[PDB]
Image: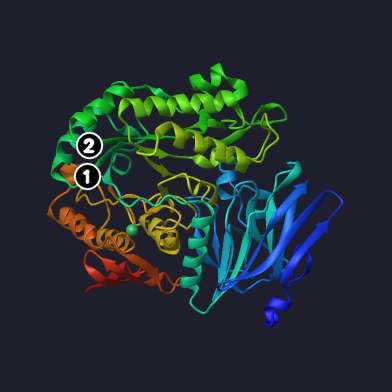
Amino acid sequence: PRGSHMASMEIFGKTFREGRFVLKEKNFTVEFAVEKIHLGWKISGRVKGSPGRLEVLRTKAPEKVLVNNWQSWGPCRVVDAFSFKPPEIDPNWRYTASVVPDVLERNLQSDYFVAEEGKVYGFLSSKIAHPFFAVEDGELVAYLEYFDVEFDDFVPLEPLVVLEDPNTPLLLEKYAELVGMENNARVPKHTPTGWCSWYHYFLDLTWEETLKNLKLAKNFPFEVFQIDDAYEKDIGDWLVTRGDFPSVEEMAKVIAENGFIPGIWTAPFSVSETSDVFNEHPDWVVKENGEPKMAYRNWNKKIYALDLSKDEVLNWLFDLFSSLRKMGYRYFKIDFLFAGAVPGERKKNITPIQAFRKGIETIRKAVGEDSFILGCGSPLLPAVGCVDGMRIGPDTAPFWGEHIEDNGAPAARWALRNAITRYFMHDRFWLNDPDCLILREEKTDLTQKEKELYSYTCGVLDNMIIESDDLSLVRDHGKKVLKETLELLGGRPRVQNIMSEDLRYEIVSSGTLSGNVKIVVDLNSREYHLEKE
Ligand SMILES: [Mg+2]
């Protein structure tokens, strides 16, 4: 703490300094150590009792901070911390904005990490507690939320690092490297390419349209062929199809007979009020005052959350994913995962994050080591070590999104921003999924230069490349964009000006299949400049 900033910091309520410490409080006990590491400090240890909302760190808030939403779809972006006014939270989607919405509606909240020019504060895990930062009355305060759970014996704290260097991107990358080691992150050596139905057909996908695309896909460089939301009769009833679809097993065997890795979408922690599964098993869901607690509203229905502390539920999940694996599915887009982590009443007195982790661990076991798991709508930190790929932005769209605010509604411009601002997770936490390329020439408002901007940025960043189009509408230009994109993969990217507030970014990537590359993108002008070799 030779630094004046550092002498002014507090750790578990005491003046910051190196050492080993014990805080014995009325309702809890924490034993911690503050240790020097490369680039900064690590705070680790263990806690027992009822820590509640546990204060770990306090320092004066910086004027400008990079803040991160806990899940795939929420923003990672630079915000002015003094002029901040809280958002109104949509009561149908409360918990996507925050697992602690009493914070979000009052104070600036950042989940897992927060950054300023030259300094990263970041928790290395979220296995038990939800780690977050709030700006309370001009102070940056780091908390570990234990959701009123009580611990008879010590459990480990989520470690906190405080890193300092003028190269902020390097700091973020080092932070993410430490996260990956703390959580035995899965970084596959091979990244799948593929097709996804969603961004052309949406809920109106038919099997007949699917079959046309399946035939056409033989002319495109796609390993995986993934059916999205559309095939299922209700949310929760994943093995009952509707409309013109065959059985879930039959789809897999057609897809495999055409030579693709079959993939499929589920929302596995979600059951609708109308679903067979909820109607058969009403005590399978998280509760509020003893009754089903609405987790979110979507598909014009109340959607409940499976209670992943229940063995009956985890057995059902195991059987479901085991069946899909038996059928031939080897790629799983597992969506709306925030549902499994909603606060409320569960059968076991465990945190929502502990519950969440037992559900995704079950799914991993059931599908096996040779299946690819793509997370979506998901808490980020709790999933490291389990998923192979992760959606890290809000949904893209077949339009740029000129009148779409940065509020989570679909838009190419906001999906692409998050692929930039979360670049440092890629090849550290998992493979980043920037959401699908949309390269068709009809049934879209995107220009050729917008499609290029999106696609080439994704390539430079080495992110997963999945296309979502009616392939009969993809012509020479789309095929050219896809081919050139795939040539930009394979490098080690860096967003050199991660703290930019004007949506212009300079991005380098060393050692791509096209050598050292650089792309300057402007999300406001919708322009890029790319240099190769
Ligand atoms: Mg890579």
Disc sitting over residue 260 in the figure: 2
Front one among 491 and 458: 491
**Which quadrant of the structure image shows residue 41?**
bottom right
Residue 327 location, x and y as percent? 32, 25
- Name the residue tied to disc 1: 222
Q: Residue at x 52, y 61 (%)?
A: 178
- Amino acid type assigned to the residue bearing label 1 in the image: Phe
- Amino acid type assigned to the residue bearing label 2 in the image: Phe
Look at the numbered discs 2 and 1 and tell me whether their residues touch, using CB distance below 8 Å.
yes
Front one among 326 and 243: 326
Residue 261 location, x and y as percent? 26, 37
Q: Quadrant of ligand 1?
A: bottom left
Q: Residue at x 84, y 55 (%)?
A: 24
Classify mark 2: residues with Cα within 10 Å, few (<14), some (14-19) or many (20+). Answer: many
Task: Look at the picture and state if 182 lies above or below 272.
Answer: below
Mark 2 vs mark 1: which is more N-terminal? 1
Q: Is residue 60 visible?
A: yes
Q: Is mark 2 within 8 Å of ligand 1?
A: no
Q: Residue at x 71, y 26 (%)?
A: 290
Q: Quadrant of the N terminus?
A: bottom right
